[PDB]
């Protein structure tokens, strides 16, 4: 299996030895504060040869923000993030739609085509760089909010499914309707069904055994804020 550990670039020194020991790939979150730090990117690129993807900046970003300076900053963050992704030899780059929490499904649907358009520049930059861009569900109420964005880009934009986000932030806690969007990339952890806990698999309420098995040949990112070995064991148990 292609199992990866999520970690911020700021904690790469802690992460690296654990990746090697467990045979894990990496998904490196690109701390905005570190985007200009050339040495850190070169250091990471030369030292690690496992499968690598990035998480692009997301905190307080939205291409569709009512604040035009936020819109500008968001575009710069995503584009520079992709430049760093290409530099690191990343296969995939994951990002958020920027939808605020608490939109109704109807409001979310109204964001779809404007988002599809705003993402053009970003999808095209990813294309030029040879990085696969993946939209992760965050605060979208339902998969119908994302389907038109994916369809509009005709296969150029992939989908990353985060079941905890659906459970805790959306109007669609059931993984099924999201899985119908055909995620090629999965963000894995467990939750108590209240907070985005980032627990190891097997510890919360998501019941991955009932839905994850068909997707074990796809890239799985452990988004866990504790030692990931328990989750890797869980996955190996499911794999046979
Ligand atoms: Zn994310
Ligand atoms: Zn996630
Ligand atoms: Zn998360």
Image (cartoon, rainbow, N blue to C red):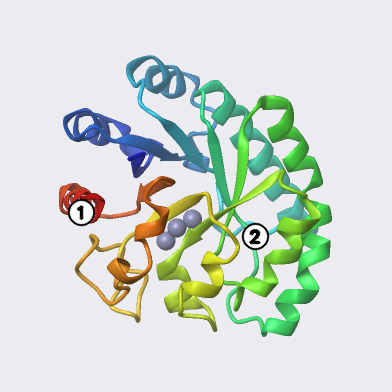
Q: Is residue 107 left or right of residue 200?
A: right
Q: Is residue 124 visible?
A: yes
Q: Is residue 10 left or right of residue 120?
A: left
Secondary structure beneath dot 1 equals loop
Image quarter where ligand 2 lies: bottom left
Secondary structure beneath dot 2 equals loop
73 or 111, nearer to the observer: 111
In the displayed structure, would residue 14 be above or below residue 240? above
Residue 226 on image: x %, y %? 20, 54
Q: Residues within 10 Å of mark 1 (few under 14, many from 20)?
A: few
Q: What is the quadrant of the N terminus in the image?
A: top left
In the displayed structure, would residue 52 be above or below residue 32? above
170 or 238, nearer to the observer: 238
**Which residue occupies 77% across, 70% down?**
111
Q: Is residue 34 left or right of residue 141?
A: left
**Which residue occupies 65% across, 68% down?**
99
Q: Is residue 205 left or right of residue 28?
A: left
| Res. 195 mark | none
In the displayed structure, would residue 166 be above or below residue 130? below
**What residue is shown with label 2?**
97
Residue 176 on image: x %, y %? 49, 73
In the displayed structure, would residue 56 be above or below residue 103? above
Which residue ends up furthest to the front in the rendered image?
240
**Which residue occupies 58% across, 25% down?**
86
Residue 109 on image: x %, y %? 75, 75
Q: Quadrant of residue 117?
A: bottom right
Q: Quadrant of residue 29?
A: top left
Number of on-image labels: 2
Residue 163 on image: x %, y %? 43, 67
130 or 48, nearer to the observer: 130
**What residue is shown with label 1?**
226
Q: Residues within 10 Å of mark 2 (few under 14, many from 20)?
A: many
């Amino acid at each position: 299996m292609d199992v990866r550990l999520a970690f911020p670039l700021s904690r790469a020194e802690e992460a690296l030895p654990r990746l090697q020991a467990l045979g894990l790939g990496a998904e490196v979150y690109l701390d905005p504060a570190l985007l200009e730090e050339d040495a850190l990117f070169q250091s990471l690129r030369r030292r690690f040869s496992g499968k690598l993807s990035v998480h692009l900046p997301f905190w307080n970003l939205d291409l569709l923000s009512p604040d035009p300076e936020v819109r500008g900053l968001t575009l710069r963050r995503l584009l520079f993030g992709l430049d760093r992704a290409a530099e690191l030899g990343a296969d995939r780059a994951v990002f958020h739609s920027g939808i605020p929490h608490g939109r109704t499904p109807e409001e979310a649907l109204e964001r779809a085509l404007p988002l599809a358009e705003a993402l053009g520049l970003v999808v095209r930059r990813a294309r030029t760089l040879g990085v696969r861009l993946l939209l992760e569900n965050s605060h979208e109420p339902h998969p119908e909010a994302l389907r038109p964005v994916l369809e509009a880009h005709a296969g150029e934009l992939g989908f990353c499914f985060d079941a905890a986000h659906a459970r805790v932030f959306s109007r669609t806690p059931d993984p099924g309707p999201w899985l119908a969007l055909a995620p090629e990339h999965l963000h894995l952890n467990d939750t108590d069904g209240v907070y985005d806990r980032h627990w190891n698999l097997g510890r919360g309420v998501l019941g991955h055994g009932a839905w994850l098995r068909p997707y074990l040949d796809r890239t799985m990112v452990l988004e866990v804020r504790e030692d990931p070995e328990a989750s890797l064991a869980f996955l190996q148990a499911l794999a046979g």
